[PDB]
């Protein structure tokens, strides 16, 4: 522990340029006997590297002498620091050769230094300059070409033979550079102030007095915190000079201004009900570390190098700019060259405790303290009352939460990508994050390249808020709200608070396009990085966003737009595309009326399943048909396509079950079939039978079973393992339209889930067999004291963070990974073909013009994925990994009789 603290102290001294203090502390440690043993060659080499970077040959020799006196041998790091100092000071070739001869006598090699010692570009250049003075013919081995994956699936994707026509952003190179500069400035600021979208009364009797007194209190708090920080820093300086270890360099690492500003921001964002003391200390320490990381990237020239590289990388995305050879964003970034350590837990904890105690001490108000000990730091009732009376309209958000205004950095590695100056991991999950990351690092780099390119593609998409829909939603939200349409009205209080955050951000991004960086989960489902964009399934959010880039509708663009409007309305679900288009043409008068006068009129859209999306589609088709040439009209609206229960689709594809394929519409058919309606009829029959037998739940739950509840139950059974969209949402859907007593809603939901599960088991034989096999395999692997692990068809390793839950989650997780691989393949092929494709909550969004091409690519990639021996490869991997278990793994479910190629002909596969 103490050795770790000392190592962290020396590393922080190196980062802060406090080599005098580091040297003093090391000399004290060496002079004191019992403390000499606590030192380590790592700390010696850290101090040596610091003195070398600063150019102190005398001090470097002194540290080497101390090392030799401590019975320690010089290592590659010490020799690297020595050579760096020699090259920096232009030392003599004689001394250089003597040092190299000593190093060779010690048994170390010169070529192994550049490979085993971690050094920056400047240090490497200085060491090479020093070496060349004695060995001018010493050149490091030339870098090899980057490796490209050649998987049976990604072969056509990464093949140079296949022709490509990737898309190009509409913004010009200069505007892209300007937006990059804006994003860089905002991320350096680290905080953004947005105007609230709540009607301001602006009174003077109470609000102005509250605001003025709060300003006075803020000034007092700031000028007290400054004094407290200065006193603490002086105390720590004296403590270190005395000999004992402290957090002086850690405090000096961040500017006093930044420290006090972050403290005040945390105090302002403190919840009224209160927050835990340990949580506050952890937050303070993590914030200090992150701000230190960003300011270090700034001062160390890393920001300048990133800007220099980005100005060139934007040539690929910019339309006017043309690169020599077309290639993926990650490939271009790696070709141009990508520029290149968490603190100890106890150090972070002590720093957080110190900062929190300093805050609690310097916080005084008319003088009584502000934070009290209830370890729960609850604010002052008077303070929260004053803040409420003030009601500052501005709201503060983190630079990472706000969507980026420039193309996200391509995902070059699990760590490098997405945000600019902020480190972003590939997997969002914090449970087992260490396991996920170590597995992703262990598996071959070429394996993850597919997923990284897929994420880069999904991220490199421009978005903008729809002005009309945003204005309408704001008018409804401010005018007492409209729960019917989904707009909250002033539980509900939390929903209103959240909606205020999202709508406020929407107003901020009214006239500026943004980009959404995407990360993954342990299952493989992609999710936007910003936490405010989590609620993407809402019709409000779905109608607000639109692709900033718009393409010509083309010949079938208007037909596809009308079909999408009909699907959103949901009035004609069983009808085919021709009859849907006929109905769209029939309700053309109401569509135009809705597009012209939404608020005042027939409100036809209001009588739709998704009112906001229906209204947006009405506006779009109106603007399209009102122009001279409807095909010439440019569309910016995302058209969504989904497969009825992708989980059951994948199950049927794996089982080759003809009945299941016909039910989930895998086989060609002129009319679409609703597996939801089939399961609804089955569960209704089961309810009737159980009611005749004598079950009160079945007797009372008569007729209320509807397509919506059946869809939710199927999603929970096929895609649900206590996750978002499960039994809780089933209960919510039931209550929302519940005319029966709510006392047994929980039991009714349980019974419905059970009956739907049994009905699915009875109907889908292949699904039943595959689910039973996976369940038994997971159960046995858990009984053997191991966690279930596998590899997706693409190559991404997947592990379960749960530490039976594994038994119940293995089949859903496998199906999720299959769907994610299918989506990644479809997205990669669309990007190769020059299409704008995104995945938003199991619904593929594209443009109205390229819907046919997207569906074709989806069918082709689905057949390609399910043509490989997925189950056989899974069984072989499981056996090789965990080796009665082997017997069950070998007993792969028998495949049925079904020509999977027929999927290519199915026109209702995705609708
Ligand atoms: C009421 C509902 O309006 C919205 C509005 C906007 C968003 C956005 C968003 C943010 C910025 C921007 F520029 C464009 C958009 Cl689109 C993203 C998002 O992800 O969500 C939104 C929701 C709302 O805030 N909700 C939260 C509580 C649960 C939800 C539900 O109905 O269950 C509803």
Image (spheres, rainbow, N blue to C red):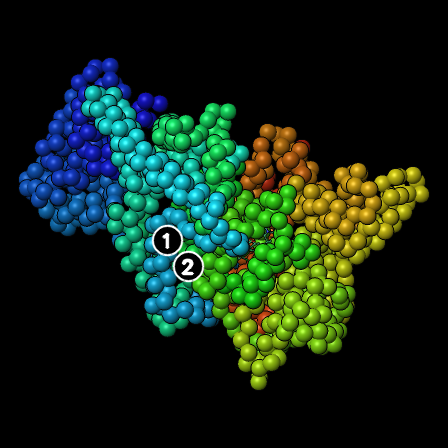
Label 2: state its secondary structure: loop
Query: Quadrant of residue 748 in the image?
Result: top right
Q: Residue at x 45, y 53 (%)?
A: 194
The quadrant of the image that shows the C terminus is bottom right
Q: Is mark 1 on a helix, strand or loop?
A: helix
Q: In which quarter of the image is residue 328?
A: bottom left
Q: Is residue 507 visible?
A: yes
**Side of 475 relative to 366 (left or right):** right
Q: Which residue is drawn at 38% across and 28% down?
A: 367
Up/down of 511 relative to 420, above or below? below
Q: Mark 2 points at which residue?
A: 405
Q: Looking at this view, is 154 or 890 the one in front?
A: 154
Q: Position of residue 228 (x, y in %)?
A: 30, 30
* Whether residue 892 is situated above or below residue 645 in the rendered picture: above
Ligand 1, seen in the image, is in the quarter at bottom right
State left or right for residue 60 relative to residue 828.
left
Q: Distance between the residues labelled 1 and 2?
A: 10 Å
Q: At which x and y percent is residue 469?
A: 58, 64
Near mark 2 (Cα within 10 A), the count class, few <14, some 14-19 or many ≥20, is: many
Residue furthest to the front in view is: 205
Disc 1 vs disc 2: which is toward the camera? 1
How crowded pointer 1 is (Cα within 10 Å; few <14, some 14-19, many 20+) is rated as some
Q: Is residue 488 left or right of residue 461?
A: right
Asked if residue 149 shows in the view, the reply is no
Give the mark, 1 or 2, whose residue is nearer the N terminus: 1
Q: In which quarter of the image is the N terminus?
A: top left
Q: Which mark is residue 186?
A: 1
Q: Is mark 2 within 8 Å of ligand 1?
A: no
Question: Residue 765 in the image: x percent, y percent?
Answer: 77, 49
Instruction: Tell me: is circle 1 under 8 Å from ligand 1.
Output: no
In front of the other: 572 or 314: 572
């Amino acid at each position: 522990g103490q050795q770790q603290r000392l190592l962290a102290f020396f590393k922080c001294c190196l980062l802060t340029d406090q080599l005098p203090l580091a040297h003093h502390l090391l000399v004290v440690h060496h002079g004191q006997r019992q403390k000499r043993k606590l030192l380590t060659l790592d700390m010696y080499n850290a101090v040596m590297l610091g003195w070398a970077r600063q150019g102190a040959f005398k001090e470097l020799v002194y540290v080497l002498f101390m090392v030799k006196d401590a019975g320690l041998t010089p290592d590659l790091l010490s020799y690297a620091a020595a050579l760096q100092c020699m090259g920096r000071q232009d030392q003599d070739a004689g001394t250089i050769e003597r040092c190299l001869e000593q190093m060779s006598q010690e048994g170390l090699k010169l070529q192994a230094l550049f490979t085993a010692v971690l050094l920056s570009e400047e240090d490497r250049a200085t060491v090479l300059k020093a070496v060349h003075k004695v060995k001018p013919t010493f050149s490091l081995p030339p870098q090899l070409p980057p490796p490209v994956n050649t998987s049976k699936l990604l072969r056509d994707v990464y093949a140079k033979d296949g022709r490509v026509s990737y898309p190009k952003l509409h913004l010009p190179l200069k505007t892209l550079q300007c937006l990059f500069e804006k994003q860089l400035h905002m991320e350096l600021a680290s905080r953004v102030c947005v105007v609230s979208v709540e009607k301001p009364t602006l009174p003077s009797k109470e609000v102005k007095h509250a605001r003025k007194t709060l300003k006075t209190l803020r000034d007092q708090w700031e000028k007290a915190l400054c004094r407290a920080l200065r006193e603490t820093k002086n105390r720590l300086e004296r403590e270190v000079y005395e000999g004992r270890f402290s957090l002086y360099p850690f405090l000096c690492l961040l500017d006093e201004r930044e420290v006090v500003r972050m403290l005040l921001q945390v105090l302002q964002a403190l919840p009224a009900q209160g927050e835990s003391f340990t949580t506050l200390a952890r937050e303070l320490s993590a914030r200090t570390f992150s701000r230190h990381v960003v300011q270090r990237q700034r001062v160390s020239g890393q920001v300048q190098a990133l800007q220099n590289h980005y100005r060139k990388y934007l040539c690929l995305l910019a339309s006017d700019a043309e690169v020599p050879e077309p290639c993926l964003p990650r490939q271009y970034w790696e070709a141009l060259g990508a520029p290149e350590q968490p603190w100890p837990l106890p150090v972070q904890m002590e720093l957080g405790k110190l900062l929190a105690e300093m805050l609690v001490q310097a916080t005084q108000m008319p003088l009584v303290p502000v934070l009290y000990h209830v370890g729960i730091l609850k604010p002052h009732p008077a303070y929260v009352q004053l803040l409420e009376k003030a009601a500052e309209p501005t709201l503060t958000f983190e630079a990472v939460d706000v969507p980026m205004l420039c193309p996200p950095l391509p995902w070059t590695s699990p760590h490098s990508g997405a945000f600019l100056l902020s480190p972003t991991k590939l997997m969002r999950t914090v449970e087992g994050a260490t396991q996920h990351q170590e597995l992703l690092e262990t598996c071959p780099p070429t394996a993850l390249h597919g997923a990284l390119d897929a994420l880069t593609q999904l991220g490199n998409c421009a978005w903008r808020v729809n002005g009309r829909v945003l204005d309408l939603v704001l008018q409804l939200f401010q005018a007492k709200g409209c729960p019917q349409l989904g707009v909250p009205a002033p539980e509900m209080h939390s929903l209103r608070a959240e909606a205020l955050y999202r709508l406020s951000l929407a107003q901020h991004l009214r006239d500026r396009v943004f980009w959404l960086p995407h990360n993954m989960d342990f299952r493989g489902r992609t999710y936007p990085c910003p936490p405010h964009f989590n609620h993407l399934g809402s019709d409000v959010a779905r109608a607000l966003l639109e692709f900033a880039q718009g393409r010509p509708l083309g010949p079938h663009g208007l037909d596809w737009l009308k079909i999408h409007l009909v699907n959103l309305t949901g009035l004609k679900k069983r009808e085919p595309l021709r009859k849907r288009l006929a109905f769209a043409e029939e309700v053309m008068d109401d569509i135009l009326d809705s597009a012209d006068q939404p608020l005042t009129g027939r409100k036809w859209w209001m009588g739709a399943e998704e009112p906001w999306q229906t209204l947006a589609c009405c506006m779009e088709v109106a603007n399209a048909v009102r122009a001279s040439d409807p095909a010439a009209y440019v569309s910016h609206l995302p058209v969504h396509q989904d497969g009825s229960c992708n989980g059951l689709q994948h199950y049927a594809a794996l089982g080759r079950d003809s009945v299941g394929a016909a039910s989930v519409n895998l086989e060609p058919s002129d009319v679409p079939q609703d597996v939801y309606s089939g399961v609804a009829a089955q569960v209704e029959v089961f309810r009737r039978q159980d009611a005749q037998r004598g079950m009160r739940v079945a007797q009372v739950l008569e007729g209320f079973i509807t397509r919506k509840v059946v869809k939710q139950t199927v999603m929970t059974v096929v895609y649900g393992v206590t996750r978002y969209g499960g039994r809780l949402q089933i209960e919510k859907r039931l209550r929302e339209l519940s005319d029966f007593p709510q006392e047994f809603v929980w039991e009714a939901s349980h019974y419905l889930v059970r009956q739907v599960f049994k009905s699915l088991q009875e109907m889908f034989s292949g699904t039943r067999a595959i689910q039973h096999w996976l369940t038994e395999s997971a159960r046995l692997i858990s009984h053997m004291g191991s966690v279930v692990e596998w590899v997706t068809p693409l190559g991404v390793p997947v592990i379960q963070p749960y530490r039976r839950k594994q038994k119940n989650g293995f089949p859903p997780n496998f199906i999720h990974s299959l769907d994610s691989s299918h989506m990644m393949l479809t997205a990669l092929h669309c990007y190769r073909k020059g299409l704008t494709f995104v995945s938003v909550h199991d619904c593929y969004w594209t443009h109205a013009a390229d819907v046919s091409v997207m569906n074709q690519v989806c069918r082709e990639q689905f057949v390609r994925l399910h043509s490989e021996p997925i189950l056989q490869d899974l069984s072989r991997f499981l056996v090789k990994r965990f080796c009665q278990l082997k017997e069950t793994l070998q007993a792969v479910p028998k495949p049925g009789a079904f020509d999977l190629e027929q999927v290519k002909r199915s026109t209702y596969f995705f609708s």
